[PDB]
Length: 269
Length: 269
Ligand SMILES: [Zn+2]
Ligand SMILES: [Zn+2]
Ligand SMILES: [Zn+2]
Ligand SMILES: [Zn+2]
Ligand SMILES: [Zn+2]
Ligand SMILES: [Zn+2]
Image (tube, rainbow over all chains, first blue to last red; front, side, top):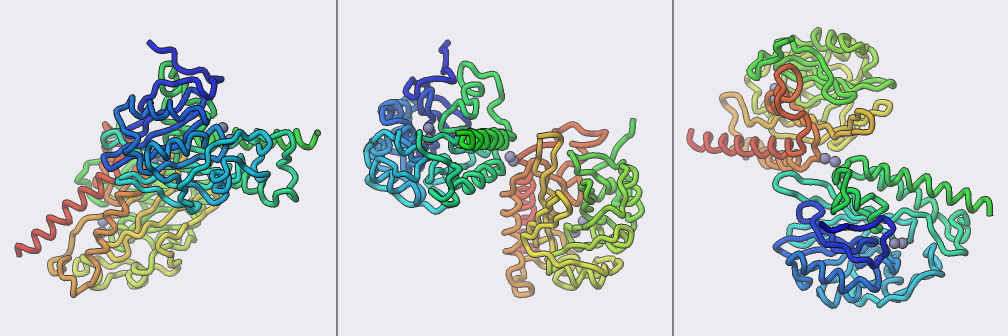
């Protein structure tokens, strides 16, 4: 029997790919999520993990008996190197356009963010993405019978996006939520509380927390799987249920408390 | 132990009032639904059953320890005498406005429908409603923390409306759906297939079936409780689960099949 993943697992430590629910499959690493949403008309790939994880994600798609060339759309949580890192490599293997919101596009085109990113100074360089479709803030990415809806989730980054869709096992159909990172982390310089440096940014982070808290949410997954206890719910170490309709609420409420603690830290220093 | 209700129960046969889920309570009869949605800021009453059921609904509210005078809004599924029959009586006891969609207002004001109602010729007279608020087709009725959303559901009548809201037991919160009647029943004269007599009516009935099928639906209740198997899910005869996320879909699909059978009957006669 396999050991499964730790919650402190390296971003590049391999994970056994596997079904999450229905036609939603996990194809990331122990430390970083990536999902494959499948149909007989083509698939949607969710995220690209790190710049080092591209070959793992492709091997994982194949391990499940799907072909990367059948992916017709790639979507992104947020424009940090640990989620966007292998996008260009994945676009080459799949031929699929990458969908992102307007505030993420320059970063995806440069392969590096600008000062609007809380983590600007600690960014790692990644390959520019050649073909990006700018998606509206509640736009829908459609491939055959698949429909993934964007939920704008700025705060951890300007371009952050959560995603929601329905997956079914027979007639038991569940609202999947891939909620973006909500951690109020930064480089050594950035101050969430300095509104004059980025007017409205922190308010929009608060708005994001409220929006994510309100989603219809049967099964939550997050870009860092440990942020939603993923490995306590699927795989060899699972001991809590996969489905928990309170998960988005609790995720957002925990992130609010942590955001407020970040504000207190900034006040003190 | 009480016997509970039959599925063929008389519209006026009394039912023991009881909790459905959380702050949603059943206060109707064995044959006809009525619901009370409660808060410490006031309540919302859903439906009025028959012209004979008013005293039962008031006694049932009191049986649960709520005061009719604390109801701040009354909402309606549809303008037939078996659901709207005690509205005026209930408005007097509660002081609450009644909310209905535009196509139901004349009927509520007359106490009788016109030929737009498939069942026009078999209507029974009821008391006119004095104070009606015309509600927009996706409007929300708000009382304190309560929020009931209207889902326009024409077909069985022009004014038909389904209702949805959230009820919680602790942190386990469920999307309640009071889906309107979807039966393609009529008096002896009406023909759903005679579009020239009512242009677009049947198409809108089909649109309603699709809309109801698509609702997020954890617990379904219907104006005739047997149409959703209510008494197989709550009360003394319960043997199936209260929560079934497939219920709206199955309800609407069964109604589509029955609508199509009505069309075949009309073709044959
Ligand atoms: Zn990040
Ligand atoms: Zn990350
Ligand atoms: Zn749900
Ligand atoms: Zn009716
Ligand atoms: Zn009826
Ligand atoms: Zn649901």
